[PDB]
Amino acid sequence: KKNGYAVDSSGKVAECLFNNYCNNECTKVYYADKGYCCLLKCYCFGLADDKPVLDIWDSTKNYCDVQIIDLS
Image (tube, rainbow, N blue to C red; front, top):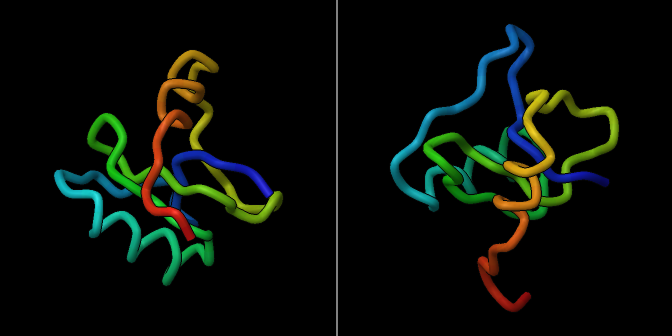
C-alpha cells in the first residue's frame, strides 16, 4: 500500500481545512487506513497500490508523511 493525495475518477482531490473530514474521505471512499489535511488537500495513509494519487513532488510527499494521526 502507498500514501498520497487520492483523486476521484475525474482526477480531482478533496480540498480541506480540517483533518477529520479527510480521514472520513480517505477511509470511507478510498478505503485507506487513515488520512489528514496536508497543505489543504486530503492526504491518505495506506491506500491500495492501484489507487490513483496526485503526481506531486517527492519533497511534498515526504513532508506530508511525517505525521502521527493516532497510535492504533
